[PDB]
Amino acid sequence: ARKIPLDLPGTRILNGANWANNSATENLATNSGTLIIFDQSTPGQDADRWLIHNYLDGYKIFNMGSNNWASVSRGNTVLGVSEFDGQTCKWSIEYSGNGEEFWIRVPREGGGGAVWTIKPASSQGPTTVFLDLLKETDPNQRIKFAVENLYFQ
Image 1 (cartoon, rainbow, N blue to C red):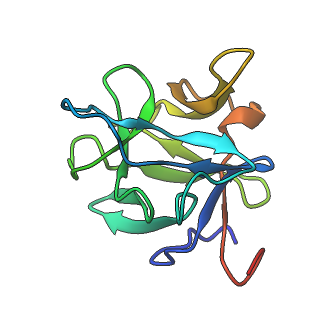
Image 2 (cartoon, rainbow, N blue to C red; image 1 turned 180 degrees about the horizontal axis):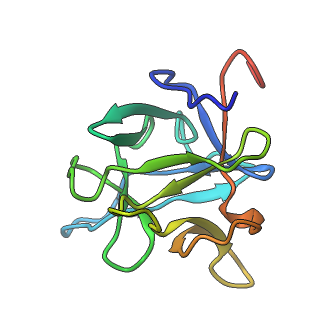
């Protein structure tokens, strides 16, 4: 509950009422990562289901449908990448102090890493994940983990 659900591959990642989806690329040329889309609809089998596991001093976040890891992009966004990279796929997961909400943060020595920030990309959506400086009162930065056979079945 202030507990991160590890090794539970049916876990949904929520911001508010929306949950995170990811899909494997259909592009032919080399792809640098796919968007993490927050909504209340799921695009493909298991696209909304995530596995969180320890990785060194942090965590790795894996999508069961896309076979991608959530990763720090070079453009201050969070994208799903098809191969694990320890330099981009490790996250700090820090309890916010409220409820069951957490911040998912770029690892940074001394703290202060930028955090997952769920925002519409345009007035027409979609709503995706950015890496912005932490504002402790910003609802768009608060992440919750909804466990299968608890909040939903």
